[PDB]
Amino acid sequence: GKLYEVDSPDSVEKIARELGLSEEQLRRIQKEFERAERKGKLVIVYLTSDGKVEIREVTSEEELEKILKKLGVDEEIIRRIKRLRKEGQIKLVIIEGSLEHHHHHH
Image (cartoon, rainbow, N blue to C red; front, side, top):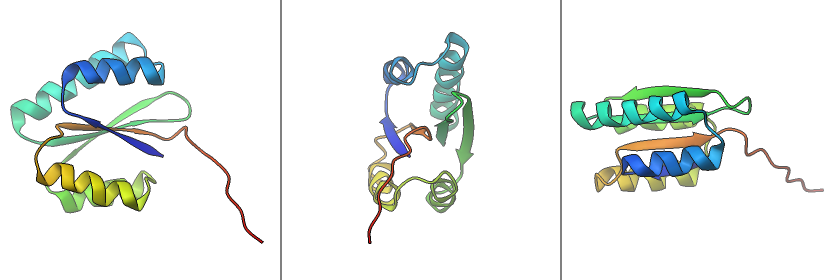
């Protein structure tokens, strides 16, 4: 699954339009985004293959790492997004679980 780096509330609407979200699912993530900014915390958001939205909060980047490991993102994303967290650039992360592909060898 892929991860989207979110720093602004308008980008939530651009990603909601890309993922095919409903108005209540958009309004949810924008409410979690302002509550993340108000409380000084990072929030993780997931889109399922069924088009459901799910939310998780973190205290520390070691919890963030354990959640990204649970959500099945690539290890590049876990270490790379951690550098954006160290620079404090991202207020919210959005993740897509519908992005399944095949790769095989002899």
